Length: 134
RNA sequence: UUUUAUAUAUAUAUAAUAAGGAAAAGUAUUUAUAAGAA
Image (cartoon, rainbow, N blue to C red; front, side, top):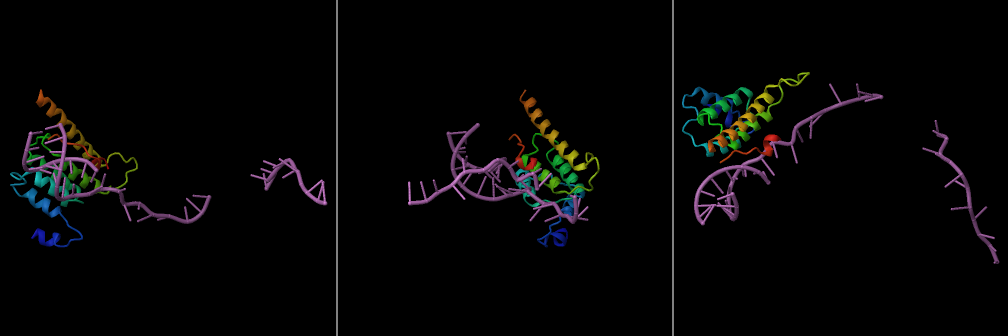
């Protein structure tokens, strides 16, 4: 029913019902191939709302068992694209407490921890891309 | 482009994928001075 309500209209594809369904669903994204999934998510899922993006980030983390190292570059591109497409809720006069920038940074230290943990494991690698910076 | 996939011996060949869209009105003194003709 979710697909019929929103996705049939090509101009605006609302994936918030989809992310809500899979979050409520117990299976979540587990036992799904990382790679075909990551490319599909990046390709099709965009212009999500914030609460949907938080659920997406958490569900990808749980799918990949919390291994920050495994969290692929496409996963970053998808989350960062969704966060960038968001407009500010309001232009705060100071303009430093925005939720989006905080989550964006949080993913950045997650990438740094991924590199550090892989190197300490020594004792593919994810890449930061120009799309994320943009 | 970028990233990734399959295959092959860190690298190579093919396939897919592209983040750059912002709207608004009003806010003079100029300078020195070179002419040719039969």
